[PDB]
Amino acid sequence: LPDDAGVTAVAAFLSSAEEKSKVMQAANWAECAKVKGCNLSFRLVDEAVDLVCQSKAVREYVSQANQTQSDNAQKGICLVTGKAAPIARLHNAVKGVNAKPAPFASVNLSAFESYG
DNA sequence: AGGAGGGCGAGGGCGATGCCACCTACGGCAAGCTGACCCTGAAGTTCATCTGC
Image (cartoon, rainbow, N blue to C red; front, side, top):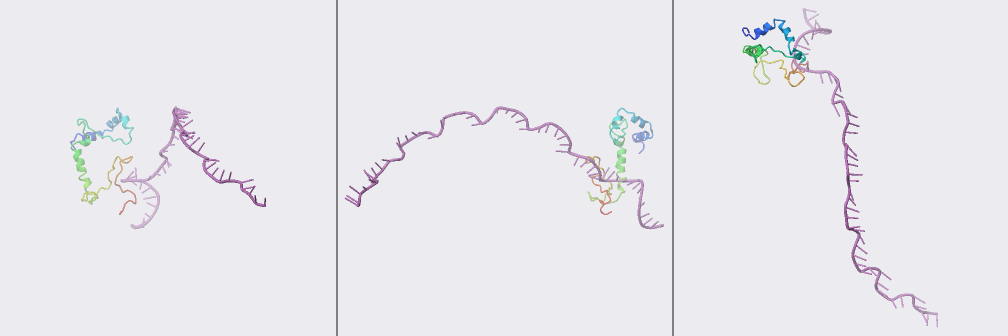
Protein backbone atom coordinates (compact mmCIF):
# COMPACT_ATOMS: atom_id res chain seq x y z
CA LEU A 1 0.00 0.00 0.00
CA PRO A 2 2.40 2.72 -1.15
CA ASP A 3 1.92 6.44 -1.79
CA ASP A 4 -0.33 6.76 1.26
CA ALA A 5 1.66 9.27 3.36
CA GLY A 6 -0.06 7.72 6.35
CA VAL A 7 1.57 4.31 6.33
CA THR A 8 4.73 5.48 4.59
CA ALA A 9 4.82 7.91 7.50
CA VAL A 10 4.50 5.22 10.16
CA ALA A 11 6.68 2.78 8.22
CA ALA A 12 9.22 5.60 8.36
CA PHE A 13 8.32 6.03 12.04
CA LEU A 14 8.74 2.29 12.66
CA SER A 15 12.12 2.36 10.90
CA SER A 16 13.33 5.12 13.22
CA ALA A 17 14.17 3.65 16.67
CA GLU A 18 14.55 7.25 17.91
CA GLU A 19 11.18 8.92 17.40
CA LYS A 20 9.75 5.81 19.03
CA SER A 21 12.21 6.56 21.82
CA LYS A 22 10.81 10.10 21.77
CA VAL A 23 7.38 8.55 22.31
CA MET A 24 8.50 7.48 25.79
CA GLN A 25 9.73 11.04 26.36
CA ALA A 26 6.24 12.45 25.85
CA ALA A 27 4.23 14.64 28.19
CA ASN A 28 1.60 11.99 28.91
CA TRP A 29 3.60 8.83 28.18
CA ALA A 30 3.83 8.24 31.92
CA GLU A 31 0.06 7.77 31.98
CA CYS A 32 -0.04 5.25 29.14
CA ALA A 33 2.69 3.26 30.84
CA LYS A 34 0.29 3.02 33.78
CA VAL A 35 -2.39 1.20 31.78
CA LYS A 36 -1.28 -2.33 31.00
CA GLY A 37 -2.01 -3.31 27.43
CA CYS A 38 -2.22 0.27 26.21
CA ASN A 39 -3.14 0.40 22.52
CA LEU A 40 -1.26 3.15 20.72
CA SER A 41 -2.18 4.10 17.17
CA PHE A 42 -0.55 6.26 14.76
CA ARG A 43 -2.67 9.22 13.73
CA LEU A 44 -0.50 11.05 11.24
CA VAL A 45 -0.88 14.78 11.43
CA ASP A 46 -2.79 16.51 8.59
CA GLU A 47 -5.71 14.10 8.97
CA ALA A 48 -6.62 15.30 12.45
CA VAL A 49 -9.28 12.74 13.34
CA ASP A 50 -8.33 9.99 10.93
CA LEU A 51 -5.82 7.40 12.03
CA VAL A 52 -3.18 5.93 9.79
CA CYS A 53 -5.52 2.93 10.00
CA GLN A 54 -8.45 5.10 8.88
CA SER A 55 -7.19 6.41 5.53
CA LYS A 56 -9.06 5.32 2.42
CA ALA A 57 -6.28 2.96 1.56
CA VAL A 58 -5.82 1.15 4.87
CA ARG A 59 -9.59 1.16 5.12
CA GLU A 60 -9.68 -0.52 1.71
CA TYR A 61 -6.68 -2.72 2.53
CA VAL A 62 -8.51 -4.12 5.54
CA SER A 63 -11.65 -4.40 3.43
CA GLN A 64 -9.29 -6.24 1.06
CA ALA A 65 -7.43 -8.11 3.82
CA ASN A 66 -10.76 -9.30 5.20
CA GLN A 67 -12.06 -10.22 1.75
CA THR A 68 -9.06 -12.15 0.37
CA GLN A 69 -7.09 -13.58 3.29
CA SER A 70 -10.23 -14.37 5.29
CA ASP A 71 -11.90 -16.01 2.30
CA ASN A 72 -9.45 -18.78 1.32
CA ALA A 73 -10.04 -20.54 4.66
CA GLN A 74 -12.18 -23.64 5.26
CA LYS A 75 -14.82 -23.24 2.60
CA GLY A 76 -18.07 -23.94 4.46
CA ILE A 77 -20.55 -24.16 5.96
CA CYS A 78 -21.88 -21.35 8.19
CA LEU A 79 -23.49 -22.20 11.48
CA VAL A 80 -25.11 -18.79 11.65
CA THR A 81 -26.10 -17.83 8.12
CA GLY A 82 -25.91 -21.28 6.54
CA LYS A 83 -24.03 -19.92 3.52
CA ALA A 84 -20.71 -21.25 2.23
CA ALA A 85 -18.83 -18.28 3.67
CA PRO A 86 -15.40 -19.67 4.66
CA ILE A 87 -15.37 -20.90 8.23
CA ALA A 88 -13.74 -18.80 10.94
CA ARG A 89 -11.71 -20.71 13.41
CA LEU A 90 -10.85 -18.30 16.24
CA HIS A 91 -14.00 -16.34 16.85
CA ASN A 92 -13.17 -12.80 17.82
CA ALA A 93 -12.69 -11.96 21.44
CA VAL A 94 -16.07 -10.54 22.48
CA LYS A 95 -15.20 -7.64 24.77
CA GLY A 96 -17.18 -6.44 27.77
CA VAL A 97 -18.12 -9.72 29.46
CA ASN A 98 -14.94 -11.01 31.03
CA ALA A 99 -11.87 -9.39 32.53
CA LYS A 100 -10.52 -9.59 28.97
CA PRO A 101 -12.15 -9.87 25.55
CA ALA A 102 -12.98 -13.54 25.40
CA PRO A 103 -14.04 -15.53 22.35
CA PHE A 104 -17.78 -15.83 23.01
CA ALA A 105 -18.00 -19.01 20.95
CA SER A 106 -14.71 -20.85 21.37
CA VAL A 107 -14.28 -24.60 21.70
CA ASN A 108 -10.64 -24.86 22.73
CA LEU A 109 -9.86 -27.70 25.06
CA SER A 110 -8.82 -31.24 24.28
CA ALA A 111 -12.42 -32.39 24.69
CA PHE A 112 -14.84 -29.79 24.10
CA GLU A 113 -14.05 -30.54 20.47
CA SER A 114 -16.78 -32.81 19.22
CA TYR A 115 -15.73 -34.57 16.02
CA GLY A 116 -12.05 -33.79 15.82
C1' DA B 1 -106.36 -43.97 131.73
C1' DG B 2 -106.82 -40.54 127.36
C1' DG B 3 -106.22 -36.53 126.56
C1' DA B 4 -104.45 -32.72 122.55
C1' DG B 5 -98.83 -30.70 121.44
C1' DG B 6 -100.47 -26.24 116.08
C1' DG B 7 -103.47 -24.42 112.67
C1' DC B 8 -101.70 -20.38 109.04
C1' DG B 9 -99.19 -17.37 106.52
C1' DA B 10 -96.62 -14.35 105.67
C1' DG B 11 -90.39 -14.80 105.47
C1' DG B 12 -89.22 -9.09 101.32
C1' DG B 13 -90.52 -4.69 99.31
C1' DC B 14 -86.88 -1.19 96.37
C1' DG B 15 -83.47 1.08 94.45
C1' DA B 16 -78.64 1.44 94.11
C1' DT B 17 -73.28 -2.77 92.96
C1' DG B 18 -71.01 2.89 90.86
C1' DC B 19 -68.96 7.75 89.61
C1' DC B 20 -64.18 9.85 87.54
C1' DA B 21 -59.67 10.07 85.34
C1' DC B 22 -55.41 7.65 84.31
C1' DC B 23 -53.25 2.49 81.64
C1' DT B 24 -48.46 5.86 80.51
C1' DA B 25 -43.74 8.69 80.37
C1' DC B 26 -38.60 8.36 77.74
C1' DG B 27 -34.82 6.56 74.82
C1' DG B 28 -32.14 3.13 72.82
C1' DC B 29 -33.15 -2.19 68.69
C1' DA B 30 -27.54 -1.18 67.61
C1' DA B 31 -21.90 -1.44 67.17
C1' DG B 32 -18.25 -3.76 63.64
C1' DC B 33 -15.94 -6.74 61.16
C1' DT B 34 -16.59 -9.94 57.04
C1' DG B 35 -20.10 -11.04 52.26
C1' DA B 36 -15.11 -14.53 50.95
C1' DC B 37 -10.80 -17.21 49.59
C1' DC B 38 -8.33 -20.72 45.41
C1' DC B 39 -8.89 -22.47 40.59
C1' DT B 40 -11.30 -23.38 36.18
C1' DG B 41 -9.48 -19.53 29.92
C1' DA B 42 -8.68 -18.96 24.75
C1' DA B 43 -4.94 -19.93 22.02
C1' DG B 44 -0.98 -21.02 21.07
C1' DT B 45 3.45 -23.18 21.56
C1' DT B 46 6.62 -26.00 23.92
C1' DC B 47 8.17 -30.04 25.52
C1' DA B 48 8.28 -34.49 26.84
C1' DT B 49 7.18 -38.36 25.12
C1' DC B 50 6.14 -42.34 21.04
C1' DT B 51 6.01 -44.51 17.02
C1' DG B 52 7.97 -45.69 13.37
C1' DC B 53 12.08 -45.71 10.67
